[PDB]
Amino acid sequence: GSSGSSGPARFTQDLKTKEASEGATATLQCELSKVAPVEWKKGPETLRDGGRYSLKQDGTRCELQIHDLSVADAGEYSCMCGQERTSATLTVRALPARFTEGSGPSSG
Image 1 (tube, helix red, strand yellow):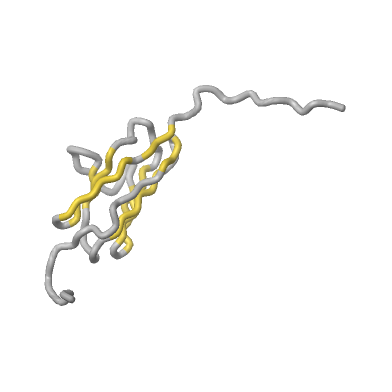
Image 2 (tube, helix red, strand yellow):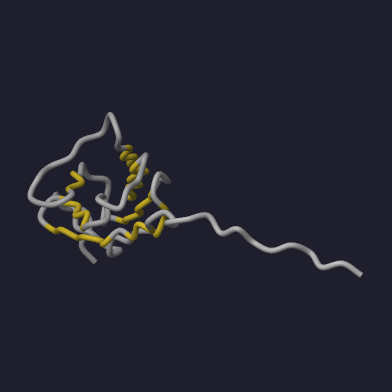
């Protein structure tokens, strides 16, 4: 086919996310047509590596991380790469209101 020809990188594998609990750390994975600089986004605003966000680029793949997860973080993370773009709704489980008491083992 056609390979030897300059051009922008386009997503190949729809970006996906995982479901973690509050305080935990999420991990999103996404593939690309080729090694190209992308930019993660959490809405009408732009994000960046450093602070409370970790974005690693493994060749044609990008692994995003969100330390200290939260119920307010659960939204829609979009990633812009060249001309194409994708998004994935992150799942954040809210902590349990109360801590189950449990039960005691019966006796003979």
